[PDB]
Image (cartoon, coloured by chain):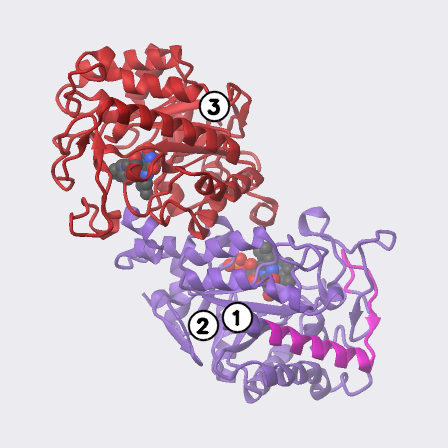
Chain colours: A purple, B red
Amino acid sequence: SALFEPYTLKDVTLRNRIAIPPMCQYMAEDGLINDWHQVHYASMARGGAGLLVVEATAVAPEGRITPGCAGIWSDAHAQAFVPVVQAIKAAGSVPGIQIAHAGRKASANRPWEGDDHIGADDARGWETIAPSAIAFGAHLPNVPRAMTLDDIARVKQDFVDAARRARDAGFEWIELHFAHGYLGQSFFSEHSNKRTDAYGGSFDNRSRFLLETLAAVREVWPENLPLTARFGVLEYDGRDEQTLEESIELARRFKAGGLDLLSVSVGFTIPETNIPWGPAFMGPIAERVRREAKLPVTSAWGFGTPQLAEAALQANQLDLVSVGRAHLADPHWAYFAAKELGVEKASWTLPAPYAHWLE
Amino acid sequence: SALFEPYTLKDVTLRNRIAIPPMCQYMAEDGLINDWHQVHYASMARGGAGLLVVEATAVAPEGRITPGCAGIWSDAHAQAFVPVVQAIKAAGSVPGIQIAHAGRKASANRPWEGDDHIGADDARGWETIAPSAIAFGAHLPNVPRAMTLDDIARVKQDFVDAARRARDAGFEWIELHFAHGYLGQSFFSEHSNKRTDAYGGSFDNRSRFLLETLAAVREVWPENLPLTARFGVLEYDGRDEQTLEESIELARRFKAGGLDLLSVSVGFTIPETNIPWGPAFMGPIAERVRREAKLPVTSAWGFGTPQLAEAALQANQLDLVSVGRAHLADPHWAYFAAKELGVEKASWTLPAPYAHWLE
Ligand SMILES: Cc1cc2c(cc1C)N(C[C@H](O)[C@H](O)[C@H](O)COP(=O)(O)O)c1[nH]c(=O)[nH]c(=O)c1N2
Ligand SMILES: Cc1cc2c(cc1C)N(C[C@H](O)[C@H](O)[C@H](O)COP(=O)(O)O)c1[nH]c(=O)[nH]c(=O)c1N2
Ligand SMILES: CC(=O)[C@H]1CCCN(Cc2ccccc2)C1
Ligand SMILES: CC(=O)[C@H]1CCCN(Cc2ccccc2)C1
């Protein structure tokens, strides 16, 4: 099975090609994770996935999506992750983290508590920041404050500090969240970036915040540990071929800047889109990015069937398959996939106190 | 769905009829549980099951099956259980524990490390005790020491101390392990009990250890929490109708002694048997115990299919269905069952950070 071959990138070796992508739990308090996250992550790691990327973890308080998001904007915040790192490692999986800044999609309610921007009169909310003072719209109508040059430098330094802390906490894999309509994605997109200084206009200027943040993080993040990013390479906004061509050139520039792997996604920059959801629908996009930018990739959004994961790998569309929601449903999904694909001694994808009895 | 109806017994209410039976993990050290159990039990509780009975926990060191078995023979051992208890409650499941003494099956290797009696040169081993100096045979050849009256008195008091400690740790449900060929089962069976004193020979004498232990425990276990036991009601040894008739009479005596519920199983007292393993094969035996002893019952051994569990409840064979190995395979099995049986808003068998996304 391709899905259960190991993967080596820099000095990290993953025991198979199953990655758990970052999935916000909205269960933190003032950025501090807790018992909820400890069991959630340790249980999934024991399930057998080779790589577990911890949810979007805010580099700054205002960079949270919700009052429940994890943060890493202080050393105390970082120290809370150590037991998660240790549990993921004890289960044989590799611990990663996604560091993030929600940009104009910040100050929102939890998804099951309205999923919408927090109102002005609710004290739990805060002012958001973005490249330009333009709202997403729809359920997120709040207009962000356009970032100053000092703002741009401060946030780049929060990403550096976040990466410094993740390193020191023991993570072996980092992912910069430049996707899904949050701060980084909104600098790259013409939809959201109307700046007239060095950080807007041309392709080079729209690229600048992302490339400078990459470069700054690269300085503190070990060369022997994978440096990755997630990026939305198209929006399904009717501008797909031009957007894709530009996104692939920026990925060429990420590679020149030392990126080891790109997690390929959708922009979600604006609500006025027509995304063709379906099983493995990102496969061909991911493949194009991989081939044209000459960079390993993962992706998500449907691949959560064992035959779809296996297929993508064999067609060299992906190097890792990210499987999210199926792990929410079953934290032992990797074991289910091993059984489905006829892996030998499939029950031993799980630790012994389980594997002995299931074989 | 019958499976997702609540159940009330004494002051305890279970949110559904899915019970997780005791399943040994063999991961403790000197009886002390650790991070393995914390995650294991908390994850399964979050999966939705109404009741989670913690694995066989030894009332005394020599009462462990293996060097990896959990213990409750001291107050520090009992304090280790408190985070487990609190984690199970936090997920909305009810915490139970099974207290146990392995009798002549003690001093054995972990199942995946030979599963056989420890050899006398191995420094890990200990002397075992039983009603009579007779070995199980097969892979468990060690001949146990015959207990004296002073031994019987001591072991009874250890069950009492264990129950007292379980109460204080916050368990809300206790199960006396009188099944599967361990100490209690071996007092009842004529195969293993050749005593000529008050604890051997007649039905009354063979029953005595079990009844006195129950009575002793009933004195310290709160009247308002379920007091239960697991008992092997037949052996498949060619003596089934007489053995089952006797077992049912003892169930009546358990009820007269305050037992609230009986977990109906097989004896496993000797290796020379022909157990007819199959899906739901205990259903009819369980039903007979329930009807004839007029006592609530659970059972296990192939109910781990949503339709099989539902059927047994609808036929009134059982009050709770114990689903073990299916929970090792998928700690969210109760969610899988609620989906299969078409339960309304099945994803909310799980907590919000999962249920929201899976509906
Ligand atoms: C609960 C939850 C939470 C989030 C997400 C999704 C879900 C379900 N996803 C997107 C996720 O990583 C993945 O791309 C999608 O879930 C699609 O993959 P599946 O179809 O679920 O296998 C995600 N994306 C990301 O980059 N960072 C994150 O923190 C989150 N958080
Ligand atoms: C790993 C493991 C460990 C144990 C068990 C089984 C397994 C698989 N079982 C028996 C268990 O409670 C249950 O009766 C069987 O697993 C049958 O139910 P299932 O078919 O698995 O649903 C069990 N029985 C018991 O009374 N005390 C226990 O501690 C144990 N330990
Ligand atoms: C922060 C992260 O990128 C997440 C947060 C919540 C929704 N994600 C996007 C999403 C859309 C549809 C289904 C699942 C996930 C983005
Ligand atoms: C102590 C407890 O009752 C357990 C320990 C391990 C095996 N159990 C018995 C068992 C036999 C075959 C399959 C599953 C379980 C008994």
Which subunit holds the residue at mark 3? B
Task: Residue B66 in the image: state x and y as whole percent.
Answer: 28, 44
Q: Is residue A130 above or below residue B294?
A: below
> Which of label 1 and label 2 is nearer to you?
1
In percent of the image, x 56 and y 34: which residue is there?
B344
Task: Residue B33 in the image: state x and y as whole percent.
Answer: 42, 47
Q: Specify whether B274 is left or right of A213.
A: left
Residue A132 sits in quarter? bottom right
Q: Is residue B321 above or below residue B190?
A: below
Q: Quadrant of ligand 4?
A: top left
Circle 3 residue: B221
Circle 1 residue: A171
Q: Specify whether B81 is left or right of B268.
A: right
Callout 2 amino acid: Leu
Q: Are marks 1 and 3 in contact (CB under 8 Å)?
A: no
> Which of label 2 and label 3 is nearer to you?
3
Q: Which residues are magenta?
A: A136-165
Number of residues whose C-alpha sits closer than 10 Å to that of mark 3, classed few (under 14), some (14–19) or many (20 or more): many
Instruction: Report how far apart the C-alphas of labels 1 and 2 lie in the structure.
Output: 23 Å
In percent of the image, x 39 and y 10: which residue is there?
B256
Task: Residue B250 in the image: state x and y as whole percent.
Answer: 29, 14
Which subunit holds the residue at mark 1? A
Task: Residue A27 in the image: state x and y as whole percent.
Answer: 64, 52
